[PDB]
Structure formats: structure tokens, C-alpha cells
Image (cartoon, coloured by chain):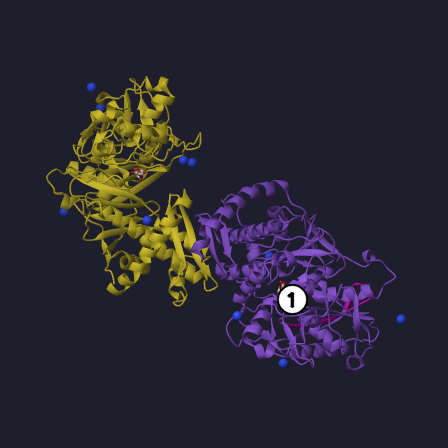
Chain colours: A purple, B yellow
Amino acid sequence: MYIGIDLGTSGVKVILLNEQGEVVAAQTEKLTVSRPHPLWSEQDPEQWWQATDRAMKALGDQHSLQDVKALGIAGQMHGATLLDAQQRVLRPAILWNDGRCAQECTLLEARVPQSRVITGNLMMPGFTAPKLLWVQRHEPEIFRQIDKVLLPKDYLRLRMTGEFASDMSDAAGTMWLDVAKRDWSDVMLQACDLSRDQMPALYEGSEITGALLPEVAKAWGMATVPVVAGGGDNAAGAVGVGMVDANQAMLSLGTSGVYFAVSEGFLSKPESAVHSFCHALPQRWHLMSVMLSAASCLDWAAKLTGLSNVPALIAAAQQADESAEPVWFLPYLSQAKGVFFGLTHQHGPNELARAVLEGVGYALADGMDVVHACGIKPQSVTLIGGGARSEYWRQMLADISGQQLDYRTGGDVGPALGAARLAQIAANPEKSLIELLPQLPLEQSHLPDAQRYAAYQPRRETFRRLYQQLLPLMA
Amino acid sequence: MYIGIDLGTSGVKVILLNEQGEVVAAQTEKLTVSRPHPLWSEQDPEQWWQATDRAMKALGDQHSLQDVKALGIAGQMHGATLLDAQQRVLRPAILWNDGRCAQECTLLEARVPQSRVITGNLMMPGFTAPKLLWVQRHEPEIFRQIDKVLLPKDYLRLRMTGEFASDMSDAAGTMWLDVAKRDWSDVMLQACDLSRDQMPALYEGSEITGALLPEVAKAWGMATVPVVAGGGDNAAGAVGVGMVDANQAMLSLGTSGVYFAVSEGFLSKPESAVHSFCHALPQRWHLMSVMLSAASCLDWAAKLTGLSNVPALIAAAQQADESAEPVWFLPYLSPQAKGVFFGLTHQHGPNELARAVLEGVGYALADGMDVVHACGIKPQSVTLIGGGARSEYWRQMLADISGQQLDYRTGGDVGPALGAARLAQIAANPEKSLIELLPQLPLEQSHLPDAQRYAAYQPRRETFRRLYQQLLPLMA
Ligand SMILES: O=C(CO)[C@@H](O)[C@H](O)CO
Ligand SMILES: O=C(CO)[C@H](O)[C@@H](O)CO
Ligand SMILES: [N+]
Ligand SMILES: [N+]
Ligand SMILES: [N+]
Ligand SMILES: [N+]
Ligand SMILES: [N+]
Ligand SMILES: [N+]
Ligand SMILES: [N+]
Ligand SMILES: [N+]
Ligand SMILES: [N+]
Ligand SMILES: [N+]
């Protein structure tokens, strides 16, 4: 028996994994988000906890615990949690999707011209370091009282164990990590006027950080089980799925589009949207990129076409007629807008639906290509989330992208599964890592049709040209 | 009684008019088109005849033609029929929608610097003259044998009468005609290595060119009746609709979109996409421009939005969310039309979409008319006909957008065959006035521009034009 916790943005999910890969029980609790001025996105750590606590007990009361040998954590990345010397919350956490600190990203990069090299990343307002420059510039009374900065999942760890600890995948997201070295950068820390004194200790995701406190273990109906370092949600997710070694990758077709690809050692393209982090396992790194959200776009397209749903939209796409010429659908994730180009008399809601599917696919494919151009070459890609559910569209995507696309079972549990697996790892020291990294069961595999792939390439050239030409119009 | 024949592209139509000018009977026969190569559009002139024969025979079953007093023809314009000295058909007819001779179009304009001045037109591959340069250049063996070049309806005439003749409206479409002078242009003909001897005799539409041959008359159950010159399909259509004097104008929102306006004498502004020809009546001239098929668009906006019928649609659009930002529909006129939906957001469903189509087609049509008007046409009203014209809502929208009074009438169904018959009427009743014999169709409803909605539309028209231009190069 193992426990995985995921500290999400919309809420907390906790699971119970069996000695096998089976999830036995699951509980979920909602979080709210706060927005007290513009570009601000905040939560309070206490609510993180109260929800987590609440969840573990819902969990306890659904199935028996105390068979549990280990517990792992995951969470939303990049969140600044500031603690005073008593371990009291200095101010509400500043989240990944907070945008207050643009000017500070600038200064930070100016103070450390080698920052892109050290971190392997473009500085963003949602990353941790610049948030801290912001506090010191604006909330100095608060800045002066800082004893520690934790990432959100590591706040939970504190409450859970009394230790200050992170994993490499999360810490990588602070911009205080030397990603190549898997250790803090004194240069980056100083420039924010901080020291290692104020960082948590660094672990690999599979490593033990401590154990439940007696109190907490009592509250929860279980022993002082060991707690592992865990990961950031995307990495922990990938661990869950089995995407753990070089050139393995997964594409998320849900509400929150992401491509995640394990790299052959550390790589970077620091002047792009391609970010590079430690994985939540020893000796691994990954790339990742925000994408077109397929699920969002299909939802909208459904309404736009008047087909009132996605399954209906996909169904209709299948009915489109094959002698009609290509229409091009151009989606602009940027504020969720679009263009149909090349409409003729031969184009009904069917044709229109096909064009939506193809154009989302055109975009997804190009997004993947961008990652790959950084030095990743997948043998296949694993497909998760709501838009992965159609057999027709999986095949389209493979034909367009030229990737073998894998659909697996259980791809849908989220980072919590990864956190649980990490626990299971640490609890089986006798076995090698490589005997301990299950992939999810292969439910269907989609190889690209060579003719269809070839016919799509020129359409993709056309897509790119049109997207490019109209972009400044839709902006 | 009277007969009108319309030699179309996709079929022939014959009609029987009574003394009072009503259609008493009609008959249609289908035609195929042959496309041996990309950009080639051809028909066998023999198929024109067999189709016309069939049709007239069928007509006669329905009703005796023994009391017909005159006969008229109209036809698909610009078709090149090449005959030898024995009236042998030398090759298949190269039609108006053939695009094989673009190069020749340029060559011709280079050769005859004043060509746009003489023809009143910019040279198009659909026009007759460049077609003949192409044959000269690509089929010299054929060219060597040319005795006669006939437009399609005029080949029909020869088969019916044994005469070689055309009218000013069809002849204008050759690019060999001096449109100002209503006579062939030696300059234009020479430049193609042709002479007047290779052209038919020219008439006005309403003049008699001959009579049915006995064998033909007999086969069709009629007298050796007099035959008028007729018109090209557009001009003949206009005559049927009563479009007849300077600044009369019609907009056909049918399966084939046209704006047709009778001008004050001859008007030349070629630089441009307005065409200028002779009208099928004496001392009459006209401008024309291909337009969107508002009909074949409205139908599409319907099925597109999965709306059922042209009034489902027109109704969806009125449920359009006022607070929604605009979707922009940009329809690009090639029949062939290609469209863009620009600026779609979360706010948009089928109601919005349907609104966008109406307004965008509207915007296109208004700009289309403006261009023609800028040439020197000033209508008191615009006659509005065709299946596209059926919606009251849209007709008004069109008026609001355009600033133009739109007169809705019924009965533009019949087509060029009507005008053809009207022409025969004229010739057969030489004492009667055109006022008498060429009435307007029934006025159904007159749409005046709403001053408030017109003003509201103007900035949208400006915006449309801006956007349309921007994407224009992308539509090739
Ligand atoms: O549109 C025009 C060209 O002037 C008509 O000629 C039709 O092409 C058929 O006659
Ligand atoms: O992936 C990251 C970090 O780059 C964030 O946690 C968001 O994706 C949450 O949706
Ligand atoms: N709460
Ligand atoms: N044990
Ligand atoms: N400062
Ligand atoms: N279906
Ligand atoms: N009469
Ligand atoms: N055909
Ligand atoms: N063609
Ligand atoms: N001559
Ligand atoms: N006779
Ligand atoms: N312009």
C-alpha cells in the first residue's frame, strides 16, 4: 500500500495505490484562488493544508490505511511560500500563474547575465526567484522576516514531517537551481539577496525526506510512514505514466495543454517557450512546453459549429466528404479565437468539423516539432486527457505529426500516481530503479499512415503560412 | 405567338409566348461540357443543334407552334465556333469559361495598345479574340482552314436559317467589335490575322436576319418564320426584365450573379473589372460585372450552419447577440467563390455566423455596385431579382448597407429566352412601341435605405474593405 498526494491549483487529490499499480481509493478537495489586485494569483498555505488533511481523512474513511508503507507528494510548481522564523506564513503564496513581477524578471536577468545559462530557462513572472525580488522591493517589512521559501508541495511536507526539503524537479522551477548541477546557484540566490540558509535541502524524487509526525500519523489512521521527495506535477505525472527515460514523451490533450519530453541528459533552448528542468528521478532531465489546449478548443469549436459537444463534433468530422477541398482552421490561443480560410460551397458542418480537428492537429504537431528541435527524438508519444478519447482523432494526429501515438489506461489519475510510485520506489531499496518503473498498460497504439502523412505535409506548410500571415490581425 | 430560344452552357431552353407576351409553354434539354485538359472547356456545336431540335419538338407536343409569327435566340457569350469554307466544324467550340489563352490575352493587348479603347474592355481569356490567337499558335493547321467564326447562338442561327449573322451585344463580346461604332474593328481583326470576311453580318437585336429554312420549319411544325438577331444571354435577359434605358439597372441574386446597368451611351473605364458592351437594342449600351451568387451563398450559409432553409437562416441571424463583437465574413469571388470567417471568439455561435454571412455578402455586393456606378452609372432604383432576392429581411439589409433603393420584382425565372422572344415580338410588331412590348416585371416591394442603419453600416463597410484587401493576395 502507498499514498500519493497532489497539491493542485484547483484542488488536492490523494490516492491509495496497491502493491500493484491499482489505485484503491481516491479523495479530492477543492481549493479557491485569490486575486486581490491585478496580475495577482494567490493561495494560503493553511488552506492547502486544511484541504490536504481533510482529504487524507476522507481517504482513511473510504478504505483502510496503516498497511501503508510510504507516502509521496506532488504539486503545482513555482509557487513562492514565505515563512518566518516560527514557521509562520509571512503572506499568501504567490502562484505559478501570478503575473505581478515582470519588471523584476528584467532586473534579475540584468543582475545575472548568465542566468539563462545557469537555469537553462527564460525567466517568467510565474517562476519563483523574481517573485522574491518583488517582495523585497514592495513588501520589504515582509522580505526581512523570511526564514525560508518553500514550493507549495514542500510547504505540505513541512506540515507533514517538520522537515524543509524539495526535489530536483520542483527546485529546478525556482530559478535558483543550477539545473545542470542539480544543486543551488549561489549566484542566483545572492542576486535575490538570499542564501542557501533560506532554501530547503535538495533530494532526488525517489529519496526519503523524513516521516510523518506522530500527531499527523495519528490524525490520519496510519504509522509514521516515510515521506519521499516527490516532484513538481508535470514530472510526477510523467513518473506516473512511465515516461522516465531519454526520448520518452507525453502530450496532454486536456484543458491544460503540455508537451513533456525526457531528454538525453540536460538540454536547453533558453530563448524560447521550451523550458528545461530536472526530472523527479536520479540522473534524468526533461523539456516541456505549453501547448494549444485541445479540449478547450474542441469545446469551443463544438459551440461555434452548433454541434453542442465534442463527441458530436468528432463524429461529424468523420462524416465529412473527401472530395471537397481543404478548409483551414486557424486557432489562436493568443484570447481563444480563430479563422476559417478557404470556405467553399462544398463545406458543411461536417467539413467544418474536420477542419477544426486538422488545424488543432496542425498546431499540436508544430509545437512538438519545436521541442524535438531542441534535441529530442521520440519513438512514440503517450496521449493523455480528455481529447485523447477518440480513436479517429488519435489516428489523425499521428498521420499529421508523424509520431506513433500511444493511448494507455489510467493516464488520467494525474501527478498523484507519480507521487505514489515514488514512494513505492523508496520502499523497495532491494530492487533496481529500472525494475520499479512501470509503464501504464498499452490500450491502443497508433502508427502514422505514410500516404496520409505525406499528403498532410504540404497542408502543414499552408497552415503555417496562413497562421503567420493573419497573426498580427488577430492581435 | 412567339418563340424564344436560350442556348445556355448546361442546357437549352425554349419558350412559347402568347400574343399578350405570356409564357404559354416551356421546354428544356440538357447539355454536357467537355474538359479534355485543365482549363479547357469545350462543346460540340452539333450537340447544340440536337438539343435545340429535341426541345422544339418537345415544345410542339405540348402546344402547336403553327401560329408562331417570329423567333428569337439568345446564347452563352464569347464561344468560338470555327467553320471552314464548307461550313464544316473545324474543332470543338471553345467556351466562355475556357481559360487556356491567358498568354494570348497579354500578347493581344501588347499588340494593340489601343485595344481597351476600341473594345471598352480588359482582355479576358474567355473572350473570343485571344482564343483565335491560341488556335493560330497551337493549331496552325486548323487556323489555315478558317472561313468563319461564329458565336454559339449564331451557329444555331446558321443551322436554322442558313445565314451568317450576329447582334451587337454578342458581337461586342468577341473583342473584334468597335463598341462605340457598332461595327467590326479592322485593327482588332488584323491583329488576329482575320478579316471582316471571316465575321458574320452585324445587326441590332431586334432586327430580322432571315427566316427558318423550310426543312427546319417543317420539322418543328411551324411556318418559315422570321428570325431576329437576338442577344448575348446577359443582354437578352435584361431585355426580358425590361432593362432598356440609360441608368436602368438590375442585380440578379440568382444561380449566376450579375449586375447589369444600361448606360448613357458608350462608357469606357477598363482598369477595372467592369465590362462595357453594346446592348441588344438599337442605340443602347451597357456595363456589366460578375457578382456573387447571393442565392448560392444564402443556401450555403444555411447548410453550413446546419440551418434547414433560407428562412431558418434569416431568422437565426436576428437572434444574433448584439453585444458580441463582429465576426467578419469575407467572400471572394472567383460561380467559384471562396470565403473567410475572420475574428471568431467564444462569443460566437450559428446565429452570429449567420449574421456575418448576410452582412459580408451584403458588403461585397454593395462595393460591386459602387464600382460600376463609378464608371458613370446613376440608377434611380435597382431592380432586384433571383432566388437570392427572396428574403425581405435581407433585401432591406441590402438597401441599408448600400444606400440604394431596391425594387423587388417576381418573374426573373424565365431567363434570356424571355428577352429573345421579346425581341421577336418587336420585329413582328414594328408599329408598336417598346414601352408596349417590353414591360417591367411586377413590382412586389420597394426597399428604401434606412438612414440610421445606413450610417451604422458605413464604418463596417470601411472595415470590410480594409480586411478584404488585406487577405486578397492570399486568395490568388
Ligand atoms: O458572364 C458573362 C461574360 O460577359 C456572360 O458572357 C457569361 O459568361 C455567359 O455568357
Ligand atoms: O506546468 C507548470 C510549471 O511550468 C504549472 O504547474 C502549470 O502547468 C499548472 O497548470
Ligand atoms: N474552505
Ligand atoms: N515491514
Ligand atoms: N530598486
Ligand atoms: N457517434
Ligand atoms: N389588346
Ligand atoms: N458535364
Ligand atoms: N474550366
Ligand atoms: N478585307
Ligand atoms: N413547300
Ligand atoms: N489599399
- Please state if B62 lies on the left or on the right of A417 as rendered: left
Front position in the image: A464 or A130: A130
x and y percent of residue A322 in the render? 53, 45
- Please state if B74 lies on the left or on the right of A327 as rendered: left
Total labels drawn: 1
Q: Which residue is mark 1?
A: A189
Please provide the residue range marked out in magenta.
Answer: A11-23
Q: Is residue A308 above or below residue A85?
A: above
Can residue B177 be seen at all in this image of the molecule?
A: yes
Q: Secondary structure at mark 1?
A: helix
Circle 1 Cα neighbour tier, 10 Å, few/some/many (<14 / 14–19 / ≥20): some
Residue A469 magenta-drawn? no
Q: Is residue A130 above or below residue B75?
A: below
Can residue B89 be seen at all in this image of the molecule?
A: no
Q: Is residue B243 above or below residue A306?
A: above
**Quadrant of the image containing the C terminus of chain A:** bottom left
- Please state if B258 lies on the left or on the right of A78 as rendered: left
Quarter location, residue A298:
bottom right
- Most common SS among magenta residues: strand
Tell me which image quadrant ligand 10 sits in: top left
Front position in the image: A446 or B417: A446
- Please state if A67 lies on the left or on the right of B244 as rendered: right
